[PDB]
């Protein structure tokens, strides 16, 4: 599935981009910048809110582009990896 | 190719976010960027660290979510197709 | 569409139930209890967190039952009401 | 009727939430009810007012979301069908 591979790579690149942005512009530790990016694009949300106007505008754009990529990856992960794995693990052998 | 469905979803989304920006900046007294941010993280379900302080703002937010959530995720989906397709196609027929 | 009518009534009943619960057990004003119920079941989330163990257990159960009802209603609202309305409003007359 | 798909999704969900309850109560030092609550509002995307305080807890949460979000919404959907069907059917063939 080349669609799954592309969504995987773009999701990785997206989370790297957010990690770099929030550590640089919002001053977060990289691990906190990564956490922020993940919980934002999965729509879980965080206690942390961007403090700068640049962070706020970026996050708006990051949200609209990133949700579609991340949930596209999550759907393909479920269908192509997790579902076949569960089915295989339910087979009596 | 021209994607009218995408173009209309884009227009509807932007109009919906402008309406929220106007409401929260005037009724809840937020800066425009904060009113837009609240509008976005509400309709995408990310969620705000801020809560409306007025009953009017709370009632508007409830209605805003039901009027807008479907439109916004419709737009996110069509945006995803348009943004991701060049990468997918470049990895198919280079 | 009787499926839409049922989901509508159940969503109303669900939000009334949450309004009554959070005002009684968590001491919220009714409007704040309603707000909490709505943003919780739409997964938006709130700054308010249940303080009592009863509120926490109820909210867990309310979330699992309520998300499915509310997003079922939202999907039918989009398909049966909002989409036809938008299409009708795009017709040149 | 027996809905094995629902039964398995239920089992997977409960096991996933137990794993999160154990992790957050031991690594992040939460009461079990708070660890379960965090686990639930994370995987349903409602979101927590609490953030993990340890790097280990932050890394686990990232992986937890990707391992669990799909399963949990699969379960929410099947639960919705089973919970709503009696009301729908009672309003069809009373
Ligand atoms: Cl501004
Ligand atoms: Cl406990
Ligand atoms: K959410
Ligand atoms: K959220
Ligand atoms: K939140
Ligand atoms: Na918060
Ligand atoms: Na908060």
Image (tube, coloured by chain):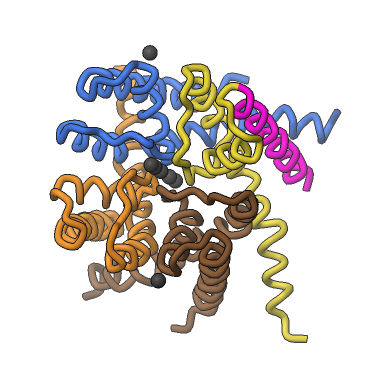
Chain colours: A yellow, B blue, C orange, D brown
Which image quadrant: the C terminus of chain A?
A: bottom right
Quadrant position of residue D94: bottom left
Relative horizontal placement of residue D39, taking residue A4 as reference (left or right): left
Residue farthest to the right, as pictured: B94
Quadrant position of ligand 6:
top left
Residue C90 visible in the current orientation: no
The correct choice, above or below, for C54 with respect to C48 in the image is below
* Residue occupying image coordinates x 63% and y 31%: A18
Q: Which one is nearer the viewer's eye here, D21 or B5?
A: D21
Residue farthest to the bottom, as pictured: A93
Quadrant position of residue C66: bottom left
In the rendered structure, does residue C41 fall within the stretch colored magenta? no
Q: Which residues are magenta?
A: A1-24
* Residue occupying image coordinates x 45% and y 69%: D32
The correct choice, above or below, for C82 with respect to D88 in the image is above
* Residue occupying image coordinates x 64% and y 40%: A31
Q: Main secondary structure of the magenta part?
A: helix
Q: Position of residue D57 (x, y in %)?
A: 59, 54
In the rendered structure, does residue A13 fall within the stretch colored magenta? yes
How many dots with numbers? 0
Q: Position of residue D26 (x, y in %)?
A: 56, 66
Quadrant position of residue A28: top right
* Residue occupying image coordinates x 23% and y 68%: D91
């Amino acid at each position: 599935d080349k669609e799954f591979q592309v969504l995987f790579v773009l999701t990785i690149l997206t989370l790297i981009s957010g990690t770099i942005f929030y550590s640089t512009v919002e001053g977060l530790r990289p691990i906190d910048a990564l956490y922020f990016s993940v919980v934002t694009l999965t729509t879980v949300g965080s206690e942390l809110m961007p403090q700068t106007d640049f962070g706020k505008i970026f996050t708006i754009l990051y949200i609209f582009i990133g949700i579609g990529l991340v949930f596209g990856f999550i759907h393909k992960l479920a269908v192509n990896v997790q579902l076949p794995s569960i089915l295989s693990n339910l087979v009596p052998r």
